Image: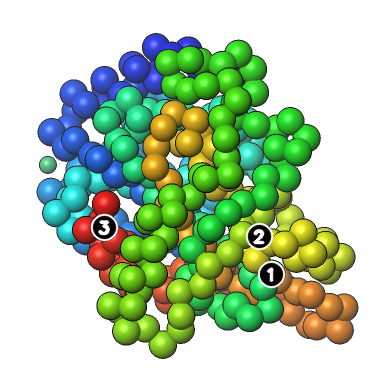
Amino acid sequence: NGYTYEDYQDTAKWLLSHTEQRPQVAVICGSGLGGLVNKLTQAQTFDYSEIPNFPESTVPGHAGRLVFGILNGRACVMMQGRFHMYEGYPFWKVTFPVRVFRLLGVETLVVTNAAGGLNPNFEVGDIMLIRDHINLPGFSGENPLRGPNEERFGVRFPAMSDAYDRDMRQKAHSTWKQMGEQRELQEGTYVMLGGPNFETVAECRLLRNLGADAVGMSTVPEVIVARHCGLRVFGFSLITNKVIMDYESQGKANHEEVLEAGKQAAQKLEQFVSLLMASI
Ligand SMILES: O=c1[nH]cnc2c([C@@H]3N[C@H](CO)[C@@H](O)[C@H]3O)c[nH]c12
Ligand SMILES: [Mg+2]
């Protein structure tokens, strides 16, 4: 790390004193998913740049704003845009907001992201509930929890086998049924790698063989820090593109189309998330 416990406190107290909102839920909006803040009522926005100690969103499709508001009668705070290791941020910076949210009184964290589909049965536009994850950078020691442990947040060796709340994923499926959607709510394992380049065909095949259903360059570190500090976690990936799996294909992954997919699914995702508020 690099932040002191007081640093998180300072930031939390700053927010608590600049808004009347008191969120119980925090939502992290991934690439092209900033539209999830659109239906919040009594909304109050803070650019990340005005919040002490907050990193900056430099990726297109990430507004870089913290939006407090009410969603379906639930007080929430949304990260309209997030941070990634490939931007040059160590995980202790990428996940700074998560601990701030805990110090604000938040109890649940909803993580979302745009991801490449590895499961051949996935189609662009699909919503995949994250049932589990594979932390590749963690295998190497790249972890937000690396270094002295802050007992005021959590224990030295947190368990991750139950990271994605079982109860919330049951409600997610029940709720999806109420939406009367054409496609079924997908569910699977999200694997995180560093980026920023998109994967090669050989890497794609290997990742699928590891048992991964979707691939991305975010989320996992946020989930680890969330669980460490006691937050209930729920999340999903919007399958924005199908990773190229063969050498005969003329396709090629690109951020522009990833952002387009997010816009086309934004509406359906908003309703789903809003409906879910009632479940929390
Ligand atoms: O096929 C993919 N591989 C790796 N990342 C992504 C993404 C996510 N969106 C960004 C790039 O489109 C980046 O932050 C990554 O986490 C979408 N599709 C893919
Ligand atoms: Mg206001």
| Tag 3 near tag 1, CB within 8 Å | no
**Among numbered discs 1 and 2, the one appearing first in the sequence:** 1
Q: Pick the residue in front: 196 or 226.
A: 226
- Above or below, comparing residue 93 to residue 200 in the picture: above
- Can you tell which quarter of the image residue 274 is in? bottom left
Type of amino acid at the residue the image marks with label 1:
Leu
Q: Nearer the viewer, mark 3 or mark 1?
A: 3
Is the residue marked by circle 3 packed among few (<14), some (14-19), or many (20+) residues within 10 Å? some
Relative image position of residue 80 (x, y in whole percent): 38, 49
Residue at the spot of label 3: 279
- Above or below, comparing residue 6 to residue 146 in the picture: above
- Can you tell which quarter of the image residue 177 is in? bottom left
Q: Secondary structure at mark 1?
A: loop
Q: Secondary structure at mark 3?
A: loop
| Tag 1 near tag 2, CB within 8 Å | yes
Type of amino acid at the residue the image marks with label 3:
Ser
Q: CA distance from mark 2 to mark 3?
A: 27 Å
Residue at the spot of label 1: 118
Q: Residue at x 79, y 64 (%)?
A: 209
**Ligand 2 neighbours mark 3 (CB distance < 8 Å):** no
- Can you tell which quarter of the image residue 182 is in? bottom left
| Tag 2 near tag 3, CB within 8 Å | no
**Ligand 1 neighbours mark 2 (CB distance < 8 Å):** yes
In screen coordinates, is 30 left or right of 257? left
Q: Residue at x 63, y 39 (%)?
A: 85
In screen coordinates, is 242 left or right of 81? right
Quadrant of the snapshot with the N terminus: top right
